[PDB]
Length: 179
Ligand SMILES: Nc1nc2c(ncn2[C@@H]2O[C@H](COP(=O)(O)OP(=O)(O)OP(=O)(O)O)[C@@H](O)[C@H]2O)c(=O)[nH]1
Ligand SMILES: [Mg+2]
Image (cartoon, rainbow, N blue to C red; front, top):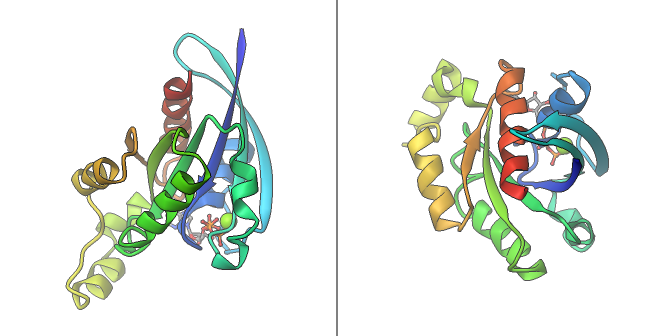
């Protein structure tokens, strides 16, 4: 049985949503930022004991689209709440805003927390730039703690830029959780 699964990604502008989808579905990384309006992707993968067909909905992180974004939440198997690990702020109150929008659509919808750009954890520009904000990249441990406080089923993370296998792994796990 080829199982079918609808996943929606949401999160702040530039947090890494499209980069993940392009890697997963097109084996393509976009080094230059092009803001998303809306896009759909299709990916097939094997998830443990199943072939799964993923229907993936890419949304804009911009508040300009707040009135129209919830329309893609219908009949979703999970919403992937994404954040940039290098920006303890796409996390901060913003993941609360994001979590509430998903709750306000339907409290029954499953939420997975996805950390993006994990390669920036050891990047020296990121480290210093954040240090004089008295901050540091989000660690794996912090990701898990955030997932708990946002009622996400799991924290998963990757790097679209340096590890395509980290991305395929996120979506394999996401699919098993929805099956
Ligand atoms: N260092 C690093 N940069 C990344 C990674 N993934 C994406 N980026 C960078 O961040 C930019 C923004 O990524 P996107 O995927 O386009 O951002 P987005 O979440 O889709 O943003 P919106 O469409 O505006 O909501 C990319 O063009 C890359 O320059 C990553 O894994 N590591
Ligand atoms: Mg995008």
